[PDB]
Image (cartoon, rainbow, N blue to C red):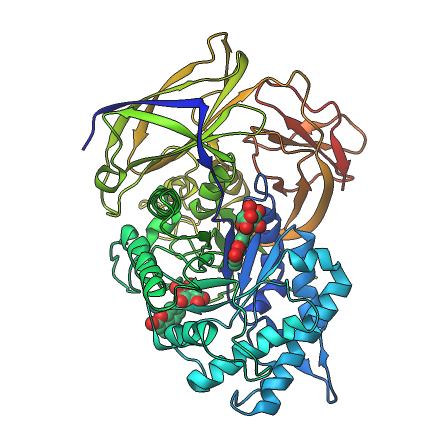
Length: 606
Ligand SMILES: Cc1cc(=O)oc2cc(O[C@@H]3O[C@@H](C(=O)O)[C@@H](O)[C@H](O)[C@H]3O)ccc12
Ligand SMILES: Cc1cc(=O)oc2cc(O[C@@H]3O[C@@H](C(=O)O)[C@@H](O)[C@H](O)[C@H]3O)ccc12
């Protein structure tokens, strides 16, 4: 419902601060953290620009513990699970949840309540020692998930004592460790209302002296109900129900109403493992961004509430059509790598969309559009930000709730108010033609000829090595056009964009700092086996600094010969899966800025 829009973004005019408030994902159960598939996934998840994903919300961490007869527990599985997060620069959004060796049966029994308190205290004590208390203090702790679905039994009172025990457990070591909840699934459920009453008036069953503290309020609100049918996400209703909850707090518990509000599981549709094919396509990138933009425009900007964090729950392991950030190819079903079944994973739009969004800056700029933008009616939305050091990062979102709608509009994008001097314009796109590995896969001929030679089919369930190389080129956030460098003496740039429905476009306009970018650091190389037992190496590294619009190449030397490039697309994330390394392989990673300059140093190892 629009043909051409002229959009002017004025980088010289700051409107308000901008936070990237969506930098989280999650999955269940905690045991996946011990599997090699998840280990590989965490390299991609921890490699987004500027901590583009920072928190993992993993269910049933305490099922990793078991009672060692006595006071304590065998911590060794939990240690491995937390260590993999920390090692990939991820932090737990730590749900105090699970039941070590089934020991907990009754939260009204005050000896159990006290034992739970002691478990929480022991957790904080151990991990504060293992990683440092500075690390611990960057975490968030949460109540056990739902509790308004299959909360074993325990009741409202059990729940409220459980909360008390969590809070007293953290307070024994450090009261500044943030605690919140209830992480309820249904809007204004009994559990939710009860915890709010308890934390407002109400008194802790372990102290006896006022309500237990609450540092944030968390709920799950999702776009549409679980179904085998492709029901249509209602994205604006997520914000409507969140504001309803806030209204409930303003009326009934005004002392809590200004607290940080968290949607700890914000997905377009309930039921991750149902098959909804749009999870593999640009629709999902569009819709994640659309949900984000609605929260920014309707909650944060007018200050209707202190909305602080939105976590997706899309790091489950599964196929193209499930709510997963990778498509898993291999023999395992989740609904030493020489022991376990080999596998390949391909990035999907749930992750690439977050790669693009991770590039956003820290300040909202003024934007004017003609005709004026009306995202709730026609689907064209914008997140226009200024980067530290100058320049802009703009997300242009063309997304509607309906899955089955296509089309395109024209945008003339103008950016003014830049500091004069050269700038580079980088255009990244997720749509049907770009960053589109599922489309590529569907068009690949299945060489196993499962319907015989006269009926070729696509979508090979076991792609060839060459097919996988084609998918891995397509899986990376793609340049819509080659980067252009503009000598903008007037501090203006402009560009024409063809904007499909659905699509996500990231426009980066970055100044020339005058020197090559900083070299990458901390290169880790690990062995995996791909489908058919093919040798593979996963590379993970860190950016040399916080510069915008940095792209990485991966090179290979054998066994001393000069380095040749082995990455296909320029990488914006600090992770790369390499297939079939030669003998005596040495890896090197180079950073490239948008002006074509290579980091003077490459980072080596193997
Ligand atoms: C769960 C939760 C509660 C809360 O009050 O704040 C959070 C902040 C979270 O991310 C931080 O959000 C911004 C901030 O609080 O300053 C960002 O600027 C931080 O970098 C980020 O860690 C994640 C989870 C929560
Ligand atoms: C059973 C159930 C009832 C309900 O009213 O709401 C729910 C919300 C739920 O939230 C999340 O849903 C899952 C999903 O959407 O597939 C997962 O994303 C999360 O693990 C779960 O916490 C899970 C179960 C229920």
